[PDB]
Image (cartoon, rainbow, N blue to C red; front, side):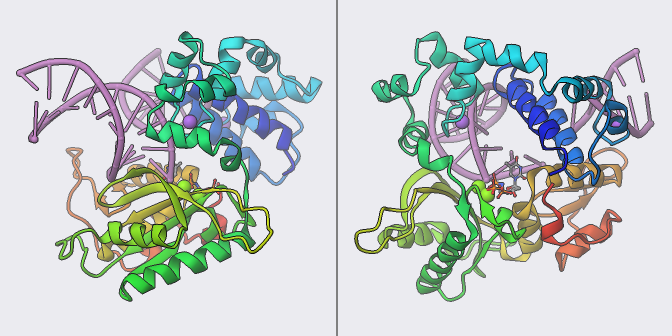
Length: 326
DNA sequence: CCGACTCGCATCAGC
DNA sequence: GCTGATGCGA
DNA sequence: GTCGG
Ligand SMILES: Cc1cn([C@H]2C[C@H](O)[C@@H](COP(=O)(O)NP(=O)(O)OP(=O)(O)O)O2)c(=O)[nH]c1=O
Ligand SMILES: [Mg+2]
Ligand SMILES: [Mg+2]
Ligand code: NA
Ligand code: NA
């Protein structure tokens, strides 16, 4: 990271606009600029140099020049001193508490960690578990642990039905040396885009993982998406592993490649690829890639037989998962 | 100059 | 209960 | 906040 200081500054500004200003497009603007600078293979010398990159306009160019000259940003220094901003930015770090709820909690005088802990009855379920594992959820997961978790999930899933296929995506599939959480794609031949020949396909998997005490908590749970908490087993006299966030996503089996492309990421890579898809006259979700008729409505799903096919349509060279970490 | 920047689950308002 | 919007998150 | 039209 040749420009770590610059990208940190931009990320912190992105978090401000998202959590405090509640301006999601400014959040995305700052995160795009941070991303494009992160992969820039030179140590940036000026805001003008950075301005040539796509996503870096005039305003960010000015802030880069201020940072390079002084090592600080006065706009950020003020934001850090603001109490409401500081309180909201902290509260939103609890999973389940977004910008809206964070601002509402502050109005009611709930703005610290002990505040949250004494007002548990004013949290919904997701928020209560997010508070419960606040410390754990901010810890990274070494790939070594990710490999153990993959081993458990894939085997427990096989025990339920051998026709399941569990694929670990996210930063792990991109080959990250450490991950923020675990992301699992799930397929079963009974569930396709044409029909669902078996009920509770995701349920049975979740229940099995609970049965062996891998899954410990549930944030949300529906037909196709599970969002919860898991933990590795520790041997005798060991300090326990931290509790980890786990997402499980059931996708129609015939729509695997669109699914695995989506969940592999990164999130900014997905935004860029889908934006590029639009400019090429296609639209992409986790299910399909569809053309746009000039009238502006999506047409019928095009044939997809690999991840590369999706790249081919929008005229991108194929990029390995390890080169999608934007 | 300025419109525009994919979806699942929880929860709530309105009927 | 159903529908559609909002919040939050992947 | 940025940018393509
Ligand atoms: C947050 C987010 C995620 N995704 C997709 C891309 C991610 O790689 C995938 C899993 O989300 P994640 O676990 O929050 N991101 P990650 O696995 O790439 O990185 P890490 O968990 O922080 O290590 O979901 C989106 O398509 N839009 C999003 O806004
Ligand atoms: Mg992840
Ligand atoms: Mg995740
Ligand atoms: Na630029
Ligand atoms: Na949060």
